[PDB]
Image (cartoon, rainbow, N blue to C red; front, side, top):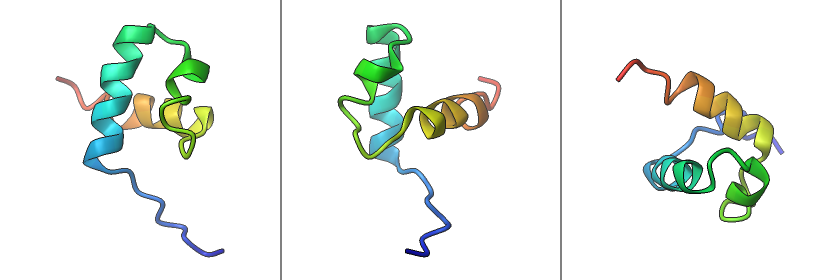
Length: 54
């Protein structure tokens, strides 16, 4: 394994947002929709990418 550049994608980002607001912040139940996305990466993503200052 040597992916390294494990960048996200439109679908994942959208699903993450649509899920997060519905579940609230139950990352365990949100990742149920995205098993290929671990909590660490999800939150890291939710903290780094989504916080682009809307």
